[PDB]
Each structure stands twice: as structure tokens, then as C-alpha cells.
Image (cartoon, grey):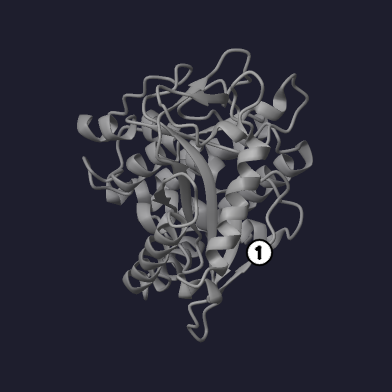
Amino acid sequence: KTFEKWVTVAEASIIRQKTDTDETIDCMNRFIKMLESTMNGISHFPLKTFKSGSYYDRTKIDYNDEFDFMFFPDMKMEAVFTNCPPGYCKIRKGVTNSKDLDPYLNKDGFLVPGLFKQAMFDLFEKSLSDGTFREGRRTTRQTSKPGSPAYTILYNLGIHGKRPIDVDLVPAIRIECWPKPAKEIKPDWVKKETTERATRCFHAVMKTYPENWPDGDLLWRISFTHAEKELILHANEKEKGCRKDIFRLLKKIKEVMKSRNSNDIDKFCSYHLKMFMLKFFDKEKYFRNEMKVDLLKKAIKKLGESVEHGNIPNYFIPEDNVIVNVLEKERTLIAKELRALLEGNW
């Protein structure tokens, strides 16, 4: 047994999962289109959606990779960043004569996450039960983590041999600029126009800030889901090498590592890998297909070192440490497990 050997099997299994990919994306495209149409007949304010996840940015490693749909009011809003911890913001009304969100504003005019969450979750539940959405009968609510931005369901397509699709419904606010505290990214590995599209907007979602903070109940998480989607989807745009292959293999490594350590890796997730990966894409200039396995080795090594050091920067806001909440016991276990993979002991 070697690392190279484990990599070969990992690649074959990733490819095996690619069967029924196009058929699945069309079921899920129909799903979200009908759900949005049902929701816009119930909500007292119009909504739009944004679709993301590994099926849409083409880094899918398993049929059951999840689908993320954000739902956001179709009106102008504004994000504020003063007195906010890195990676978080507050939300207020922009230039808009709409009073549709007024009942979710506190005395000072801030959109209150827990009030807007409860209204959006109530809307989701009503829409998935509604009679104009025949697919909602195939849906059922799944447990999510406390404070999660997502209403998580299982969508049973009825495919024998395949478990239901994991779907996150994420209430969100769309802000149509780049966040003031965010780095002006200029990756050299996508075209200038792709970076232009990636930085067109961001979204704010109601992940609860986990630490003590005055008015912390007013904090929203800055979400770069749109920009992340643009850059990952188009990562082979210029060189056409193994950039997305290395990302896919790192996600597989994480999935197997979690399966090797049932409840001891509950915080490390693909989002942390994505932030790590984007920074690796900047540091590493060359990604020839023939370099694949060696660059994966160097990526595993820098990742282990990052996790041990305990800091992986948010690619768009470098002072946001996205693994701050990953505790030492888990970080120590991750690095030890990455060392054992490289040495052929998996």
C-alpha cells in the first residue's frame, strides 16, 4: 500500500459518482424553480434565488453532495461593518420605498436575524406543504446544527439504491457590491472578466455569531458563496490542469477522514478546504496534469501545517480565521491523520 495507490482508488470512486449527474441537476433545477414559484405566491415580499454547491461548480465527488439554494428579498438593502467582528455584518434598508421588511427591523433600523429567519423558515415550511408544489410531498425536514443558516430537508427522488438528496434552503440578503472590509482579490488563474463577475455581489446569511458580543444578535455572516462559485467553477479556465482535481481529491480525503473518526471531526468541513484551496491556487503558479499527485502531496502538507498552526484565512477577508472554532483535539487529530495518509497507512 502507498499514497499513490490510495489516490488511484480515490479517483475511480470520484468518477463512479459522476453517473446520473446531468439527470440529477435537472431534477434539482426543476425543484428549485417550482419552489421559488410557490414561495413567490405566498410571501408578502418578492424573492429571488441563488444556486450553489458541488454539482453547480463541478467539483462533485459523490452523488449525495448537497444542493444549497439561497432565498433573498428582491429589494435594495445595505450592509454595515462598523463594530463588527471580521467576517460578519449588520443589515439595514437601502434606497427603497418598500416597507416589506419593516416588521423585521429593530428600533434602530437593523434587520434582526432571528426575526427574519423565523419568517423565512415559516415561509419554507408553508411552501413545501403547499398544494401548488407537488414535489414537497417527497421532502422531509432533516436535523441541522444549532444556529445554522439553513433549513435542511431530504428530497427523495425515489431512485432505488440512492438515498434522498440533501438540500439546504438558506434565507439570505443580497448586497450588490463588494464588502468594504474584503480584500480586492485579483487571482491570476481566472480571467479578468471572471473576477469581475465574482465580485459583483455578496450575500448575508443568518449563521449566529458564536461568541459574546454587544448586539451580537444583530450580526449576519458575510457569505461569499457567489464569488466562491464563480472562481471554483472556472478554476481550469486558463491553464486546464489539475487545479480542480486536487480540490476534489482533498474533499475526498476529508470525507474518508471523517468516516475514520466518527464523532471526533465534527467541525472541519469542505468550506475550510475551499478557503485553503483558493489560497493554494494563488501561491502555486503551475498545475500541469503530470504534477497532480505531487501537488496534492504539497497541498496535504501545507493543510496539515495550517490546521496545526490553527489558522486558515478566509480568502476574501484574510483576518477572518475560518477554523478558529476547530478545537485543538480535532486539529491535532487531523494533522496526524494527514501524516498517516501520506505514509500509506490508510
- Residue 70, image x, y percentages: 47, 48
Q: Nearer the viewer, residue 134 or 10?
A: 134
Q: Nearer the viewer, residue 273 or 30?
A: 30
Residue 38 appears in view: yes
Q: Nearer the viewer, residue 42 or 237?
A: 42
Residue at the location (28% across, 31% down)? 195
Residue at the location (71% across, 35% down)? 325
Q: Looking at the picture, does residue 45 appear above or below residue 251?
A: above
Which quarter of the rendered picture does the C terminus lie within?
bottom right
- Residue 181, image x, y percentages: 48, 17
Q: Looking at the picture, does residue 172 appear above or below residue 266?
A: above
Residue 306 appears in view: no
Outermost top residue: 82
Q: Is residue 141 left or right of residue 52?
A: right
Q: Looking at the picture, does residue 309 appear above or below residue 138?
A: above
- Residue 5, image x, y percentages: 48, 64
**Residue holding disc 1:** 142
Outermost bottom residue: 160
Residue at the location (78% across, 41% down)? 329
Q: Is residue 15 left or right of residue 102?
A: left
Q: Residues within 10 Å of mark 1 (few under 14, many from 20)?
A: few
Residue at the location (38% across, 36% down)? 227
- Residue 59, image x, y percentages: 40, 55
Q: What is the three-letter code of the residue carrying label 1?
A: Gln
Q: Is residue 181 left or right of residue 146?
A: left
Of helix, strand and loop, which one carries label 1?
loop
